[PDB]
Amino acid sequence: RFDNELQLRGLSVEAAVEELRAAIAEARALKETPLRVVHGKGMGVLRRTLRDYLKTDKNVESFHDAEANQGGHGVTIVNVKR
Image (cartoon, rainbow, N blue to C red; front, top):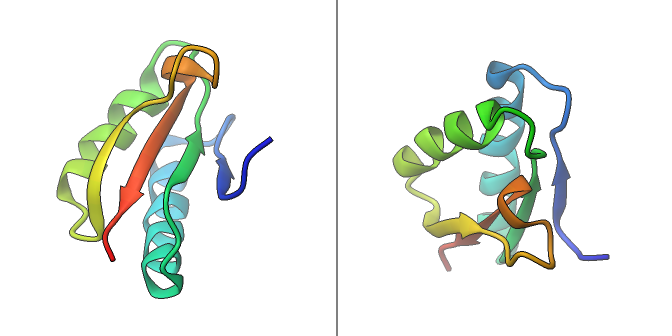
């Protein structure tokens, strides 16, 4: 269990991206980081599309897969700017 987990499994890419964009903006405002985006592994559709979005989000310092024991490539860690 972690704080700041975003549960995105079962969403469309468009809905997932919108939830993530909002969550990041909220986190920057509240000075919260890191975020754990739990999109699941699956076919990698949500991880790849979310990452493509993350490149473009000005609130994000960096992002990467979680460690293998903390969800691995089924979770994207988002480090939010201060």
